[PDB]
Amino acid sequence: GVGYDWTGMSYQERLSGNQAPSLYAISLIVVFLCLAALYESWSIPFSVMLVVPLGVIGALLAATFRGLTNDVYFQVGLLTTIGLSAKNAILIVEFAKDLMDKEGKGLIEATLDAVRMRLRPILMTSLAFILGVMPLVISTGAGSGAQNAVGTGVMGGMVTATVLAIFFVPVFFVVVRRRFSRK
Amino acid sequence: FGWFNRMFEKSTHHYTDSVGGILRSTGRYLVLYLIIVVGM
Amino acid sequence: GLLVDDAIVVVENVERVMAEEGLPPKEATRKSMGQIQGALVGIAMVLSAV
Amino acid sequence: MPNFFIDRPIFAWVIAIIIMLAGGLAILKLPVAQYPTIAPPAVTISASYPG
Image (cartoon, rainbow over all chains, first blue to last red; front, side, top):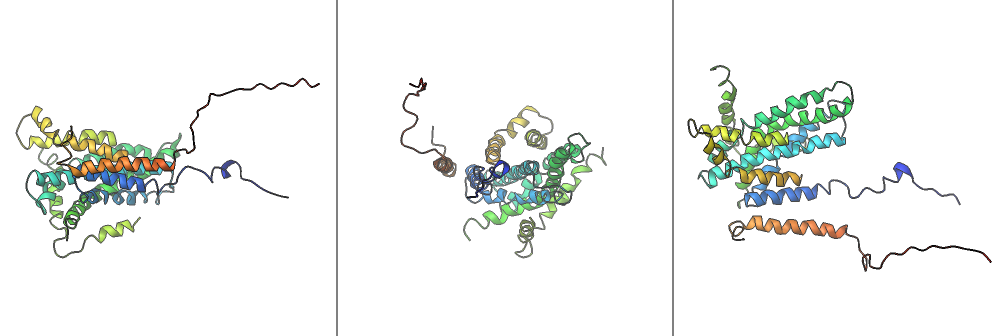
C-alpha cells in the first residue's frame, strides 16, 4: 500500500523536449548542405567543416585550466567560435577556389594567395575580439562569476583556433578535393 | 615608419613559406590534426 | 565578434585592393563587393544553422 | 526565374533537401488526431435546489 512519485526538479528530469547530439547532427547535416550549396559540390564542404575542432580544443582547455564547467555560458562562447572559425575558413576556401575557378591556378597556386590574402584580416578579428573579451576574463566582482564563465572560454577557445586554422585549414582544402574528385 | 609599420605583416611571407613545407616530402601530416580530434 | 568581423571583411578586402592600383576609393570597394557579397550571405546561412 | 540552378544543380538540390529535412522532423512533433478544434465551445452552469 506504500507508493511514491517524483516532484519538483525530479519531475523536470524525465522531460525536456529532445536532447543535444541529436540537435547537433541536424546542425551537421544542415551546415554541410549549405556549403555544398555555396561551393556547388559535395566535396569542398569537408574543407571548412574540418575546422570545427580547432576552436573547441582550446575551449575545453582553460575551461579545464580555470575551475570552470560546461555551462550554458561556456557553450554560447563555444558556438560563437565554432562558427567564427568556420566563417573565415569559408573565406580562404572561397578565395582559393575562385582564385583558380575564375583565375586559373590549382594544386598549390590555388591555396596560394588564398591563405596569404586571408591573414591580415583574421589576425585583426581574433585580436579585435580577445582584447575586449579580455576584461570579462578576469571580472571585478559584481556579478563577476558569470562574466568569467563567458570569458575564460571564448578567449581560450579563440587563440587556440586563430593560429590553428591559420596553418591547418589550407591542408583540408588540399587532400579533400585532391582526395574527393575520385582516386 | 620603416621599423613599425612594415614590422607587422613581415611575418606573412615567413608564414606563406610554412605552406611551402606542407605535405611536401611524403604522405603524412593529416595525423597531427587527428591527434587534436582525439585531443578533445 | 560576429558583428565586427563582418565589417573587417568589407574593409580589409577593400584595402588590399589599393594593391591593385595606387590611389582609387570608389571602385576599390565595389570590386570587393559582387566578388565578396555573395559569400557574406552564405555565411549567415551557415551560422544560422549553427 | 530559374535558369540559375541549371548552372548550379547542387544549390538547387540543396533547397530540395532542407525543405525535406525541415518538415519530416515536423512529422515527429506535430500533434495527431481525427479532427482539429471543430465544434463551438460551450459553458454550462449547474445549480441544485434540493427537494
